[PDB]
Image: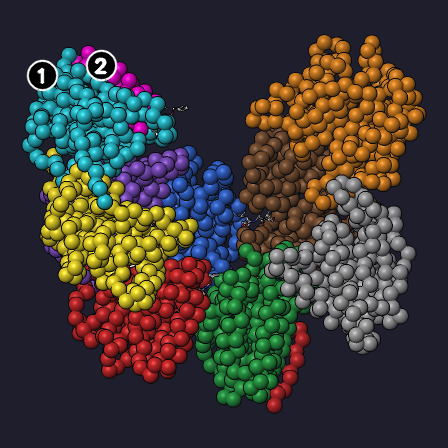
Chain colours: A yellow, B blue, C brown, E red, F green, G purple, H orange, I cyan
C-alpha cells in the first residue's frame, strides 16, 4: 500500500497504488483506494480494507448530513476532524491510516494526515502505507515549493512508481485525482504509462 | 520448523491360503494440494514380499531405501534371501531404533511365508507389529477396516459358512473398499495399485478412482 | 489393557486381554500380551506396545545369554533386576511400560512387577494396565492362597472379564497362563463375547 | 476424594458414604455427613469442590421442601432428579458453575425404588448401582460381579461390606468409617455405621 | 470449496462446487452453495456452512421486507452494503466468504465480500480454498463482454480446476445465470466425478443379525 | 476432544417408504462405563425421531429443549410437525448458541405425516442442515460408519433388508471404537408400525 | 537455516517431447521487499541437468557450490560416466533429508530437469526430503496458481511440443505476476534438450492487460 | 508419600518406616521394606522418587560392603553418612540427580548411637530424632513434646506408637502397618511390626 | 545505520553514517564503519557492532595471510568470498550485513553485498543498514550508468544525508572513501558540509 497526496496553489493531487493482499496473495489488483467523501474532498485509505471502508462510509454519512444542515460546502478540516475523532476513539480496534485532501473556498487545497493512533496534522504533502517507507528520501529530495498541478501529478506518479517497484504489497496501476475549484479529474496510469527507471545490470 | 508433514495415503493387505494382496492408492498430497497422482505406495522387496508405506513421504523414501540396503546385506552375509517373517522382525528393530525421532510411517508387509501361505504384518510408527490376516493403514484405515472384518472375518454374522477366501473375491473386496474410501476421504483417490503375491511371482494391476 | 497375576499353592497364574488401541480406535483385538521368555519364565505387557515388546525381547535375549554363560537358568529376581536396570537408563525420556515377571526359580514361584518409572517390587498378586483397578476388585474379593487349580483359572478369567466390561480400552480375548515347577502351560484363550454369555 | 455408593434392590435403596472432611493432608472431621434429606423418601449424596456441594445441595433441598409445602405432596424421585439436573446444567455455562457429583436415591409408591447418577457436567443416568470418587474404580467391578436384581437387603449390606473392605485393603486414602442408610416404603432408616 | 462469478455481456454467471468437509472427511457430497437472495440476486457461500446459511438467509429476509415496502426490485448495492455492515459488526467471527452478484436497474453487478466486512466490486471474483485455482483460469481466459455460452464454459472450467486441484472441493458443478430477463439456476450443471460401480455383492440376508429383544408398536 | 468425553454413535438410513435410526447404548466418563442403557434416540412424533450424539449432558438438554419448543409449536398450529420443519427448528435452536455451542450432532429420521415420504438429515453442532437420500452418521466412530454404509447401502430396500444393513453397519463400526458400543438399539419406522430391536453386541 | 532471510518465489517446470523447460523470476525478496532484482535462481548442473530453487537464496548458493564442485570432480576422472538427472535428484533428496534429520534444514524447494538417454526427467525436492517425479511441477504459490493450468493441459494432451510448453510456461508466469505478491516481471527460461542446456536472458511478461 | 522416623537413645537408635508401595491410587504392596542394611550396625532408610531410592540405596550399600571387604573393618556411622552425602551432592548438579530423602541410623563402638537426617538436596544433619514424609509435619511435634535424651528403649517404643497412632487418627493416607528396627551395640534387631 | 557503495570506471566509492546506538542512546556518534580489509579493499559494517568487528578482523587476518602466500594483491571477489563463508556458516549466531567494495587489477572496481544469511551478489551499487530502507526509491531514481568519481561521491553523500535525516538510528557525520588504482582517499562531511534539503511549511 502506498498513498500520496500533494498540495498546490488552488488544489491538491492524490495518488495511490491498486493492490490489496491477504498474505502473499493479491486478492484485488485493481482496487480503488481513493474514496470520495464529498465533492472536492477525498481520502486515501491504507491499512485494513474492512476498517478503512467502514470508517470512510461513516464519515461520508456524517459529513453529508452536516453539510445539508449548514447549507454550505464542507471544510476539508472538518472532514479530517471527523476522521480523527473516530480513528482516535477506536484506535485500539481500528488499523487504518488515512490522508484527507480536498478543496474548500475558505482555505483552498489542503492535505491532512491521520496515521494510526488518531493524530491529525496539516502537511504540504503526505505519504502513507507499507510502501511509503521506500520513498521518504525521494520525496524529501525532489519536493519543491510552488509546484504546479502538472508538476504535482508527475511528482506523485514518480514517487508511487518507485514504491510499487520496491514494496511487495504495492503494485498494479496508479490511480490519480486532482481536486480544485473546477472539479475532480481522475486518471489511471497502467502499463507503459507508469514512470519507468532502468534497473542496473552488471 | 516442523520436521514432519502428512502426505496422505492408504494401504491395505489381505492374506490368502496361497496368495497375498497388497494395495494402495497412488495420490500424494500436502495440505490442501495434490503433489502428484502417480506415486504408488507399494514397494516390492523380494520375489515373495511387498511392503506398503504411507505417512510422511520423506520418511517413506528413506525407510524403503534402508530396507532395500538391509535386504542386500543379509543376502551377502547369509547366502539366502530374507523371509517375510525375518523382514517383519528386522523392520521392527529399524523402526524402534528411532523411538525418540520416529519414522512417521505406517507399514504393512504382505507375502508368502516359508510354508507358501499368505502372511500379513502390520506395524506402528515405533515398531510394534503383529501377524494379522488382513489390515488397513493410512488416512482411510478407519473406513477400510470395519468392512474387511465384516466380510473377511465374518464378524457379527450368524449362520454364515466360513468359506475360504478366494483370489477373485479378495480382488473385488479390495476394489470395493477403496472405491468407497475415495468417496469420503479427501486424501485417497486418483488410482488404485494392487500387487498380488503368489508362487508364480508378483503381479500388478491398476484401476482408476475418483479425481476428487 | 488389563493384565493380572497371582501366586497360589500350585504356582502363579497369568492372564491378560488382547486389545490394542490407537487413541480411541481399536487397532487390534488379537495382541499377545504375554511373552514367553523361556519355558520357565514369561512376562506381561502393559503401556506402550512398542516399548513393552522391544524391552521384553531384549530381556529374553539377555536371559538366554545368561543361561549359556552360567550353564544354569536365570532366576526370576535376577531377570526382574535386569529389566529394571535396563529401563532405568532412559528414565524421564518418555518410556511407557509396565510388566510382570512370573516364573518358577530354584526358590519357588516368583512374581515381580517392573515399571518404566523405576518400580520393582515382589508380591503375591499384581495387576497392571488401564483396567487394573477393576481387576483388583474382583481378584481381591475372590483370591485365596489355597485355591484349587480350576478355581484359580476361573478367578483369573472372571477378573479379566469384569475389567474389559468396565474399561473402554480393554477387551478382546482372555489369554490364561499357568506357571508350574516344570514350566508354564497355555491353558485356554476365551473370547470375552463367549464369556459374557456364560456369566450372564 | 470422597466416596459414595448406592445399591438398588427390589423394594429398597441402599446408600453409603465416607465420613471424612480433609484439608491438605489432615482429617479435620471424622463424622462428616454427605447425605441430604430432600424429603421423607429422597436422599441426595453430594461430593465435589468445597462450598459448592453444600451450597448446591442446600439450594435443592430448600426448593424440594418448598414444593411439598406449596402443593401438599412431595416430589417424586424422578422429578427431583430431573429438577436437580436442570439446575446443574443451567449453571454449567454460567460464570458460577457447581462442581459436584451427585447420587439421588428415593422410593416412590407407584414406581418403586430409584437410584440416579449425575456428574458435574449434569448428565443424568438411572442405574441399579453406582459409585462416585476414586474408590468407585475399585468397587464398581465388585458390584458387577456379585450384584443381582433380586438381592435381599441383608445380602445388599453384605455386598456393601465387601466393597468397603476392598477400599481398606487396596485404596490409598484413609476412610475408616462409612455412613449407611436405606430407603423403602417406610421412609429413610439409618443403619449402623460400617467401621474399621 | 470453489465459488466463482463473472460479469458477462448481459448479466452474471455464478458457479460453485457441491462438497462440504468436516475435518478431513467428506460430509456432504451435494451441498448447495448458491443462495437465493432475491429474484434477481444470488450469493455463493464459502467458509463456515452455518455462518453462510444464517447470513444469506437473514439478508434475503431483510431484502424481501425492503422490496415489499418499496415496491421495486432490490439493488445489488443494497445487498452488498447490508452484508458488509453486518459482517464488520461481528469483527470477522462470522466465517462467511461470499460472492454476491445480480442484475438491477443500473445493470449487472458482482461483489466479493470477505468475513471481516471488506468488499470488492470486480468483473470476476473467486473465494474458498480453491479460489486460487479458479482465479488462474479467470486470469488466463477472461474477456470483457463475453457471450452467455462462453461465460458459462469459463465459469465451469474455473470451478473444475478448483475441484480437481483442491482437496476441499469436489462433486458436481452448480451454475446460476442472471440477466435482465431470465434466471437459469442449473443446480447439477455438470457431474465431472461419479462413484465407481460396486464389483461384489455384500447384501445381508435376512436373519444374519442377532436380536435380543423385539417390540412392535402399530400406529394409526 | 470434548465430543469424545462420553463417546456415542448414531446413524440413520433410508429404505422404500421406511427409515431406520440406530444408536449405541454405552454411557461413560472417558474410559469408565457407567451404564449400558443410555437413551440417545428420542421420539418427536408418531413417525419422527431425533438421535443425538456427543456430550451426554448436552444430548439431554437439547432433547428436552427441542421437545419444549416442539410441543408448543404443535399446540399452537394444531398439526403434526413435518421432518423438514423439525430440522429448521433444530438448526435454529443450535445456532442460537453459535458462540458456546451445544456439543451434539443430531440426526433426524422419519416419514412425512401426510405422504409418508422417507426423510433423513444431520446437523453440525452449530446447526448446519444436511439432507441426504442414502444415510447420515454422527458420533465418535463416524469414519468407521461411513466405510460400512458406503459399501453396504443400496437403494429401495425393504424394511427387513433395511434393518439388516443398518444393524450390520452399526455393529461393525462400533466394534472398532473404544468409547462406543455395549449394545445397539434400532428403530425401523414404517407407515403403520414402529418396531424397536436391541442387537446382540459385544460388551467389551 | 532456522529462519530464511532472502528468498525466491515459485519455480515452474514442464517436460515436452525431447526436453524439459524450467522458469523462475530473477528476484530475491527480503520479506516483502524486492531487494535483489537481478539474481539468477536457475543453475546448469551439467550438460544434461539444470536446477531451479525457491526458498533461501543463501542456501541455494551453498548447494550451487557443492553441486558444482561435485560435477567438476566427476569430470576429472574422464571415465565416461556422468551423473544423470535422476542421480542428481537422488543425491539432493538425501542431502535435504539428512539436514532435516539434523534439524538444520536447507530452506529450499528445488525443481530438477534433465534429458538423458532419450528420456525427459522432471523432479521435485522439498525442504523435508519429500521427492517425486511428475510431468509438471510448480513450487511456492505456483502450486496453487500455475499448477492447475499445467495439469489441465497435460491431462487433455499428455505430449507437448517445445513451442507449446514454452507458451504454457509464459502464460503461467503471467498469472503468477498478476496474483503472487512476491513475484517480479523479469524472469528466466531454461531449456534442456539433446543439444544441452540453454538459459534465456531476462524476459518479461509485458503482455499484461490492465483493463480496470 | 512414604514415612520414616528415627529416635536416638542413650545407647540405641530406634527407626521405623511404613510398608506401603502405591502406584497411583492402589497399594500395590502392603509389606514393603524401606530399610537397607548398610553394615552390621548401620541402616539406611530411603524414600523418594521411584527408582531413585533403590538405585541410590543399593549403590551405597555395595560401596559400604566393599569398604568392609577391602579393609577388614566396617565404616563408622559418621563416615557412612558423609560418604552418602558426598555421592548425593555430587550427583545433584549432574544430569541424573537422585530425588531421595534419607535417614541413616547406626551404632559406633566408640562414639555410640547416631541418627542422621538428609534431604534430597544432600544437606546432612545430626538430630536426636527426625522424620520424613508428610507424616513428619504431624509427628514431629509429638516427639518434641515427649522426647528426653535419657529415654529408655521401652519408652521409645511407646513414643513411637504415639506418633504412629497420630498418623492413623489425623493423616489422610492409609498406612496400616509399620516396620520397626533397633540398633544397639549387639547389632540390628527386628522388632515386631506396629500394625493397626 | 546506513552504508552505501557505488562503482565507477576505475574504482569504487564507499560511504556510511557515524552513529552507534544501544536502544535510544547514541553510544558513539563518530564511529567509523568503513574497515580497511586490505590496501585497496574496504568493508562497510552494519548490524551488530561486536559481530561485524569480529568478522572483519578474522577476514583481515585470512586475507593478509592469503596475500603473503601468493605474491600478488588480493582479489575483491576473494575478500567477499571469505566474508560469505563466515557469514553463511555462522548465520544463526551472527547479525551482520556487509558491503565489500574495492579495486584489483583483474576486475577493477567491484561492489559486493553480503546481507544477513550469508548471500553474496555483485551490484553496480549497494545499500544496507537500518536507514537503507528510506532511500531505495531515491537511489533507484537518481542512479545513472557511467558516473564519474566526483558524481559518485555526490551521489553517495546525498543518499546518506537523506537516510540520516529520516532514520533515528543514523546520524552524526558522513564518512566517504574512494578507492582506485592510485590509492584510497578518505573524506569526512560534517556540519554544513552535509547535503541539506529544505523542510515544508504546511
Ligand atoms: C483497501 C486498502 C485501502 C487497504 C489494503 C491495502 O494495503 N489493505 C490490505 O490489503 C490489508 C493488508 C494487511 C492488513 C494484511 N489486507 C486486508 O485488510 C485484508 C486482510 C484482513 C485479514 C485484515 N485483505 C483482504 O482480504 O482484502 C479483501 C479486499 C479485496 C478488495 C477490496 C477490499 C478488500
Ligand atoms: C501391549 C500393548 C498392546 C498394550 C496397549 C494398552 O495399554 N497399548 C496401547 O493401547 C498403546 C498405548 C496406549 C495405552 C496409549 N496404543 C497404541 O496405539 C500403540 C501405538 C501408539 C502409541 C502410537 N500401539 C498400537 O497402536 O498397536 C500396535 C500393535 C498392533 C498389533 C499388535 C501389537 C501392537
Ligand atoms: C459448506 C460450504 C459453506 C463450504 C465448506 C467448505 O468445504 N465449508 C466447510 O466445510 C466448513 C469449514 C471449512 C473451513 C472447511 N465446515 C463445515 O462444512 C462443517 C459442516 C459440514 C458437516 C456440512 N462445519 C463444522 O464442522 O463446523 C465446525 C465449526 C465449529 C465451530 C465454529 C466454526 C466451525
Ligand atoms: C556497524 C557498527 C557501527 C554497528 C552498528 C551499526 O550501525 N550497530 C548498532 O548500532 C547496533 C544497533 C542495534 C539496534 C542492533 N547496536 C549495537 O551493536 C550495540 C552497540 C554497543 C556500543 C552498545 N551493541 C549492543 O547492544 O550490545 C552491546 C551491549 C552489551 C551489554 C549492554 C549494552 C550493550
Q: Position of residue F90 (x, y in %)?
A: 53, 73
Mark 1–mark 2 distance (CA, rounded to whole Å): 20 Å
Residue closest to the eye, C180 or C83 = C83
In depth, the one of E160 and A151 nearer the eye is A151
User: What chain does mark 2 sit on?
Assistant: I
- Work out which quarter of the rendered image holds the N terminus of chain E and state it: bottom left
Single out the residue that lies furthest toward the bottom: E220
Q: Earlier in the sequence, mark 1 or mark 2?
A: 2
Residue B119 located within the stretch drawn in magenta: no
Q: Residues within 10 Å of mark 2 (few under 14, many from 20)?
A: some
**Quadrant of the picture in which ligand 3 is shown:** bottom left
Q: Quadrant of residue E133?
A: bottom left
Main SS, magenta residues: helix
User: Residue drawn 56% across and 86% down?
Assistant: F77
How many callouts does the rendering have?
2
The answer as to whether the residues below labels 1 and 2 share one chain is: yes
Residue depicted at x 73% and y 25%: H102
Q: Is residue B182 left or right of residue H56?
A: left
Q: Residue at x 27, y 47 (%)?
A: A122
SS type, badge 1? loop
State whether residue A183 is above or below residue H163: below
Q: Is residue F95 left or right of residue B39?
A: right
The residue carrying mark 2 is I64
x and y, in percent, of residue A111 in the image: 24, 50
| Start-end of magenta stretch | I45-70
- Dot 1 corresponds to which residue? I182
Q: Any magenta on residue I54?
A: yes
Q: Are marks 1 and 2 in contact (CB under 8 Å)?
A: no
Amino acid at each position: 500500500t502506498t498513498i500520496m497526496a500533494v498540495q498546490f496553489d488552488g488544489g491538491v493531487v492524490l495518488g495511490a497504488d491498486s493492490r490489496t493482499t491477504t498474505g502473499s496473495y493479491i486478492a484485488n489488483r485493481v482496487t480503488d483506494k481513493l474514496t470520495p467523501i464529498h465533492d472536492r474532498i477525498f481520502c486515501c485509505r491504507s491499512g485494513s480494507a474492512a476498517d478503512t471502508q467502514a470508517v470512510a462510509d461513516a464519515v461520508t454519512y456524517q459529513l453529508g448530513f452536516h453539510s445539508i444542515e449548514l447549507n454550505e460546502p464542507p471544510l476539508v478540516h472538518t472532514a479530517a476532524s471527523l476522521f480523527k475523532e473516530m480513528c482516535y476513539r477506536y484506535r485500539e480496534d481500528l488499523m487504518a491510516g488515512i490522508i484527507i485532501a480536498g478543496w474548500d473556498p475558505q482555505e483552498g487545497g489542503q492535505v491532512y494526515s491521520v496515521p494510526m493512533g488518531g493524530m491529525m496534522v496539516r502537511q504540504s504533502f503526505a505519504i502513507g502505507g507499507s510502501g511509503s517507507s521506500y520513498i521518504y528520501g525521494y520525496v524529501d529530495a525532489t519536493y519543491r515549493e510552488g509546484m504546479t498541478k502538472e508538476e504535482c501529478l508527475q511528482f506523485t506518479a514518480n514517487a508511487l512508481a518507485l514504491a510499487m517497484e520496491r514494496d511487495g504489497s504495492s503494485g498494479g496501476v496508479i490511480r490519480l485525482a486532482a481536486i480544485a475549484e473546477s472539479g475532480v479529474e481522475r486518471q489511471v496510469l497502467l502499463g507503459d504509462q507508469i514512470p519507468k527507471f532502468a534497473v542496473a545490470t552488471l | 520448523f516442523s520436521p514432519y508433514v502428512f502426505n496422505g495415503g492408504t494401504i491395505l493387505a489381505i492374506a490368502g491360503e496361497d496368495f497375498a494382496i497388497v494395495a494402495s492408492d497412488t495420490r500424494l498430497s500436502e495440505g490442501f494440494s495434490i503433489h502428484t497422482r502417480d506415486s504408488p505406495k507399494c514397494y516390492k522387496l523380494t520375489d515373495k514380499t511387498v511392503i506398503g508405506c504411507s505417512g510422511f513421504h520423506g520418511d517413506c523414501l528413506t525407510l524403503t531405501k534402508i530396507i532395500e540396503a538391509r535386504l542386500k546385506m543379509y543376502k551377502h552375509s547369509n547366502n539366502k534371501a530374507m523371509t517375510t517373517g525375518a523382514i517383519a522382525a528386522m523392520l521392527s528393530t529399524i523402526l524402534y531404533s528411532r523411538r525418540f525421532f520416529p519414522y512417521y510411517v505406517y507399514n504393512i508387509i504382505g507375502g508368502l511365508d516359508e510354508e507358501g501361505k499368505g502372511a500379513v504384518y502390520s506395524f506402528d510408527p515405533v515398531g510394534s507389529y503383529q501377524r494379522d490376516s488382513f489390515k488397513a493403514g493410512g488416512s482411510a484405515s478407519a473406513m477400510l477396516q470395519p468392512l474387511l472384518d465384516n466380510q473377511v472375518g465374518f464378524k457379527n454374522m450368524q449362520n454364515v459358512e466360513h468359506v475360504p477366501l478366494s483370489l477373485d473375491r479378495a480382488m473385488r473386496l479390495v476394489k470395493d473398499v477403496f472405491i468407497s474410501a475415495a468417496e469420503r476421504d479427501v486424501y485417497t483417490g486418483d488410482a488404485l495399485r494392487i500387487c498380488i503375491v503368489t508362487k508364480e511371482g508378483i503381479r500388478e494391476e491398476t484401476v482408476s478412482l475418483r479425481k476428487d | 489393557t488389563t493384565t493380572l497375576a497371582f501366586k497360589f499353592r500350585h504356582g502363579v497364574i497369568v492372564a491378560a486381554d488382547s486389545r490394542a488401541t490407537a487413541g480411541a480406535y481399536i487397532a487390534s483385538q488379537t495382541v499377545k500380551k504375554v511373552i514367553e521368555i523361556n519355558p520357565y519364565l514369561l512376562g506381561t505387557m502393559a503401556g506402550g506396545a512398542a516399548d513393552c515388546s522391544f524391552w521384553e525381547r531384549l530381556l529374553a535375549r539377555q536371559c538366554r545369554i545368561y543361561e549359556l554363560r552360567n550353564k544354569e537358568r536365570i532366576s526370576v529376581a535376577a531377570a526382574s533386576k535386569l529389566l529394571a536396570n535396563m529401563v532405568y537408563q532412559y528414565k524421564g525420556m518418555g518410556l511407557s511400560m509396565g510388566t510382570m515377571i512370573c516364573g518358577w526359580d530354584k526358590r519357588g514361584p516368583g512374581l515381580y512387577y517392573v515399571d518404566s518409572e523405576g518400580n520393582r517390587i515382589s508380591g503375591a498378586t499384581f495387576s497392571v494396565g488401564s483396567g487394573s483397578v477393576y481387576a483388583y476388585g474382583v481378584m481381591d474379593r475372590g483370591y485365596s492362597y489355597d485355591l484349587e487349580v480350576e478355581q484359580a483359572y476361573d478367578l483369573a478369567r472372571r477378573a479379566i472379564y469384569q475389567a474389559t466390561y468396565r474399561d473402554a480400552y480393554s477387551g478382546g480375548a482372555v489369554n490364561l497362563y499357568h506357571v508350574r515347577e516344570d514350566g508354564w502351560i497355555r491353558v485356554s484363550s476365551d473370547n470375552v463375547a463367549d464369556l459374557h454369555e456364560k456369566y450372564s | 476424594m470422597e466416596y459414595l455408593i448406592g445399591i438398588q434392590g427390589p423394594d429398597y435403596v441402599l446408600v453409603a458414604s465416607d465420613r471424612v472432611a480433609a484439608s491438605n493432608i489432615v482429617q479435620m472431621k471424622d463424622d462428616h455427613d454427605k447425605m441430604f434429606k430432600m424429603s421423607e423418601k429422597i436422599l441426595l449424596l453430594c461430593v465435589g469442590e468445597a462450598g459448592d456441594t453444600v451450597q448446591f445441595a442446600e439450594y435443592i433441598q430448600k426448593n424440594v421442601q418448598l414444593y411439598k409445602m406449596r402443593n401438599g405432596y412431595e416430589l417424586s424421585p424422578t422429578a427431583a432428579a430431573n429438577f436437580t439436573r436442570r439446575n446443574l446444567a443451567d449453571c454449567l455455562r454460567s460464570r458460577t458453575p457447581y462442581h459436584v457429583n451427585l447420587l439421588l436415591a428415593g422410593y416412590d409408591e407407584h414406581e418403586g425404588p430409584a437410584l440416579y447418577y449425575m456428574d458435574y457436567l449434569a448428565a443424568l443416568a438411572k442405574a441399579p448401582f453406582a459409585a462416585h470418587g476414586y474408590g468407585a474404580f475399585l468397587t464398581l467391578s465388585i458390584l458387577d460381579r456379585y450384584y443381582t436384581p433380586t438381592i435381599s437387603r441383608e445380602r445388599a449390606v453384605e455386598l456393601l461390606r465387601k466393597c468397603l473392605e476392598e477400599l481398606q485393603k487396596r485404596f490409598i486414602l484413609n476412610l475408616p468409617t462409612f455412613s449407611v442408610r436405606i430407603i423403602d416404603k417406610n421412609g429413610i432408616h439409618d443403619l449402623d455405621n460400617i467401621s474399621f | 470449496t470453489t465459488i466463482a462469478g463473472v460479469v458477462y455481456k448481459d448479466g452474471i454467471v455464478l458457479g460453485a462446487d457441491t462438497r462440504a468437509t468436516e475435518g478431513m472427511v467428506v460430509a456432504d457430497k451435494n451441498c448447495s452453495k448458491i443462495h437465493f437472495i432475491s429474484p434477481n440476486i444470488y450469493c455463493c457461500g464459502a467458509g463456515t456452512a452455518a455462518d453462510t446459511d444464517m447470513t444469506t438467509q437473514l439478508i434475503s429476509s431483510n431484502l424481501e421486507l425492503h422490496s415489499l415496502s418499496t415496491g421495486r426490485l432490490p439493488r445489488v448495492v443494497t445487498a452488498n452494503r447490508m452484508l458488509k455492515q453486518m459482517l464488520f459488526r461481528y469483527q470477522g467471527y462470522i466465517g462467511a466468504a461470499l460472492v454476491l452478484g445480480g442484475v438491477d436497474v443500473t445493470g449487472p453487478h458482482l461483489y466479493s465480500i470477505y468475513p471481516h466486512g471488506s468488499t470488492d466490486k470486480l468483473p470476476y471474483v473467486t473465494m474458498g480454498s480453491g479460489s486460487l485455482a479458479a482465479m488462474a483460469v479467470f486470469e488466463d481466459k477472461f474477456r470483457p463482454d463475453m457471450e452467455e455460452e462462453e461465460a458459462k464454459n469459463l465459469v465451469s472450467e474455473a470451478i473444475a480446476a478448483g475441484i480437481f486441484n483442491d482437496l476441499g472441493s469436489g462433486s458436481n458443478i452448480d451454475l446460476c445465470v442472471i440477466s435482465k430477463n431470465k434466471l437459469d439456476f442449473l443446480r447439477p450443471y455438470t457431474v465431472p466425478n461419479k462413484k465407481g460401480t460396486r464389483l461384489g455383492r455384500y447384501r445381508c440376508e435376512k436373519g444374519t443379525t442377532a436380536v435380543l429383544t423385539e417390540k412392535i408398536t402399530p400406529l394409526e | 476432544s470434548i465430543m469424545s468425553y462420553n463417546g456415542g454413535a448414531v446413524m440413520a438410513m433410508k429404505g422404500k417408504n421406511c427409515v431406520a435410526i440406530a444408536a449405541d447404548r454405552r454411557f461413560g466418563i472417558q474410559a469408565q462405563m457407567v451404564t449400558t442403557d443410555f437413551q440417545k434416540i428420542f421420539p418427536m412424533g408418531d413417525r419422527l425421531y431425533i438421535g443425538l450424539a456427543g456430550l451426554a449432558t448436552d444430548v439431554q438438554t437439547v432433547a428436552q429443549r427441542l421437545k419444549f419448543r416442539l410441543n408448543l409449536y404443535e399446540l399452537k398450529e394444531g398439526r403434526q410437525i413435518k421432518p423438514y420443519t423439525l430440522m429448521s427448528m433444530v438448526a435454529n435452536l443450535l445456532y442460537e448458541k453459535r458462540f458456546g455451542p451445544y456439543y451434539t450432532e443430531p440426526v433426524i429420521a422419519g416419514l412425512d405425516p401426510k405422504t409418508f415420504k422417507p426423510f433423513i438429515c444431520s446437523l453440525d453442532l452449530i446447526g448446519c442442515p444436511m439432507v441426504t437420500d442414502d444415510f447420515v452418521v454422527s458420533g465418535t466412530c463416524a469414519e468407521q460408519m461411513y466405510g460400512m454404509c458406503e459399501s453396504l447401502w443400496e437403494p429401495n430396500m425393504d424394511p427387513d433388508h433395511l434393518f439388516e444393513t443398518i444393524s450390520q453397519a452399526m455393529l461393525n463400526a462400533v466394534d472398532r471404537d473404544a468409547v462406543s458400543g455395549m449394545g445397539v438399539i434400532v428403530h425401523i419406522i414404517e407407515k403403520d408400525k414402529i418396531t424397536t430391536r436391541t442387537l446382540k453386541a459385544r460388551m467389551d | 537455516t532456522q529462519n530464511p532471510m532472502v528468498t525466491g518465489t515459485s519455480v515452474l517446470g514442464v517436460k515436452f517431447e525431447g526436453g524439459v523447460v524450467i522458469a523462475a523470476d530473477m528476484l530475491g525478496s527480503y520479506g516483502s521487499l524486492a531487494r535483489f532484482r537481478n539474481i539468477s535462481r536457475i543453475m546448469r548442473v551439467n550438460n544434461s541437468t539444470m536446477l531451479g530453487a525457491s526458498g533461501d537464496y543463501a542456501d541455494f548458493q551453498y548447494l550451487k557450490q557443492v553441486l558444482g564442485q561435485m560435477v567438476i570432480d566427476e569430470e576429472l576422472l574422464g571415465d565416461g560416466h556422468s551423473y544423470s538427472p535422476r542421480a542428481i535428484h537422488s543425491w539432493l533428496t538425501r542431502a535435504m533429508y539428512s539436514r532435516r534429520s539434523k534439524m538444520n534444514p536447507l530452506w529450499n524447494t528445488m525443481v530438477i530437469g534433465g534429458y538423458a538417454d532419450g528420456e525427459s526427467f522432471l523432479g521435485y525436492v522439498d525442504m523435508l526430503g519429500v521427492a517425486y517425479e511428475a510431468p509438471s511441477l510448480a513450487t511456492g504459490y505456483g502450486a496453487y496458481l500455475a499448477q492447475p493450468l499445467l495439469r489441465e493441459v497435460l491431462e487433455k494432451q499428455p505430449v507437448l511440443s517445445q513451442t507449446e510448453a514454452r507458451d504454457l510456461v509464459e502464460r503461467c508466469m503471467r498469472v503468477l505476476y498478476y496474483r503472487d505478491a512476491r513475484s517480479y516481471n523479469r524472469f528466466q527460461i531454461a531449456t534442456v534438450t539433446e543439444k544441452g542446456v540453454e538459459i534465456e536472458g531476462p524476459l518479461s511478461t509485458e503482455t499484461n492487460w490492465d483493463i480496470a
